Amino acid sequence: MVYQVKDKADLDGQLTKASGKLVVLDFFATWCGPCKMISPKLVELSTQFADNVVVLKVDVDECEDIAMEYNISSMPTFVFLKNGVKVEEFAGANAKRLEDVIKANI
Image (cartoon, helix red, strand yellow):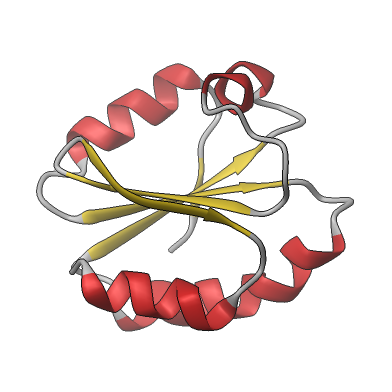
């Protein structure tokens, strides 16, 4: 219930397929402490709103082109997309802001 994209292609197809749901892009790195901390909260939210939200994990080490396209420089970074529009974006493992944004756009 927390799909990890493989490339721009796998990502683009996912956004298209994500109909009218809120899409959360999680830009992370395995070696980044803050990312490991926030992951539990991500799984919880993902499960609680399984029908109104889709979470896409993007390993910046594997998808350099995507990380570069979104101009990522801090881990973790969350980009919120709803119907092709970027409704929000912020960096950092702020569990509280993550939940507020999800509940504010579903």
